[PDB]
């Protein structure tokens, strides 16, 4: 299926994925298309920060859903 | 099977692939041989920009076929 | 299962893994979450430097276990 | 099984591999241990340059064998 990933600016990425794909898989896809490494990526859906090892279906992300992509900064 | 990947300059990458490999697989092989990240890679065949999720058979890429590899720049 | 990875400062990383995951798999997950390339990671558990090709179960790393992550130099 | 990788300097890398691993698999393991990207790696055994897609058993590389790791430079 197809999903969308948008930065807050509105720049849209289109990804082909499977419901069983993990959030990490999506992150690697964003890296493939955008050069943005996974550790710099925070993905948000339904107001929730998406966890790497959990799947798209787990979060009920469906055909043509849109995730937001947010930059993840260093802490300590 | 074997395929070729050429920059517009003529420089040739020879790859060992399967028809079920995806375009992303091929990009990864190109990274493996040339150090060029997938996100900087645009592959072209039959006039068409090749999509990461599609397979070589999907685009009728057969043995000894040549893809063109082109630099993808930052935009929006 | 869940495991923790901590630097010597105490900074804590939480990872979802399988007992059949290799030590290299774990380093790949650390890279995923922290951007530290596997070659720069040394992982230690039970005093032992952890070998890449061995599994978590090979080392009897169980759930809620903690590993130490240390910087590996040239 | 265990194999050894050495530069022409003696520095010895010890790898755990399977006879069905590809040469690319080995380069990936070298990257994991040393940070050397696969494209910068030329591996040599029995006087030949090893091909990414071929397997360790394909080259008759057995346990406790030693491969040579050689720098690959930019060319054309
Ligand atoms: Cl290849
Ligand atoms: Cl647990
Ligand atoms: Cl190894």
Image (cartoon, coloured by chain):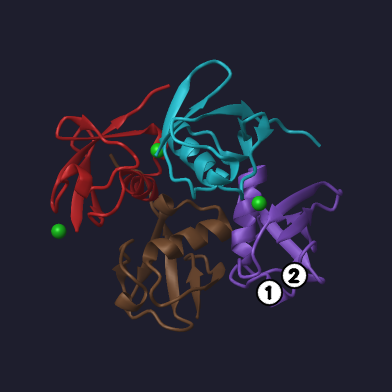
Chain colours: A brown, B purple, C red, D cyan
Secondary structure beneath label 2: loop
Secondary structure beneath label 1: helix
Which residue does the image show at 44% across and 38% down from the upper left? D32
Horizontal and vertical percent position of residue D7:
55, 22
Graded by Cα atoms within 10 Å as few (under 14), some (14 to 19) or many (20 or more), the crowding at tag 1 reads few
Horizontal and vertical percent position of residue B59:
72, 74
Q: Nearer the viewer, residue B52 or C9?
A: B52
Residue D16 image label: none
CA distance for labels 1 and 2: 6 Å
Q: Chain of mark 1?
A: B
Write down the residue under mark 2.
B61
What quarter of the picture does the N terminus of chain D occupy?
Answer: top left
Which residue does the image show at 68% across and 70% down from the upper left? B56
Q: Identify the image quadrant of residue A53.
A: bottom left
**Cβ–Cβ under 8 Å for marks 1 and 2:** yes
Q: Residue furthest bottom?
A: A63
Q: Chain of mark 2?
A: B
Horizontal and vertical percent position of residue A70:
42, 60
Answer whether residue B26 is visible to the viewer in this image: yes
Q: Is mark 2 within 8 Å of ligand 1?
A: no
Answer whether residue C8 is visible to the viewer in this image: no
Graded by Cα atoms within 10 Å as few (under 14), some (14 to 19) or many (20 or more), the crowding at tag 2 reads some
For residue D63, above or below residue D51: above
Q: Nearer the viewer, residue A33 or D13?
A: D13
Query: Is D53 placed left or right of A10 in the picture?
Result: right
Residue B57 image label: 1
Horizontal and vertical percent position of residue D27:
53, 40
Which quarter of the rendered image does ligand 3 occupy? top left
């Amino acid at each position: 299926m197809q999903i969308f990933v948008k930065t807050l600016t509105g720049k849209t990425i289109t990804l082909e994925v499977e419901p069983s794909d993990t959030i990490e898989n999506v992150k690697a896809k964003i890296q493939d298309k955008e050069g943005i490494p996974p550790d710099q990526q925070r993905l948000i859906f339904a107001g929730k920060q998406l966890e790497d090892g959990r799947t798209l279906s787990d979060y009920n992300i469906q055909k043509e859903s849109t995730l937001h992509l947010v930059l993840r900064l260093r802490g300590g």
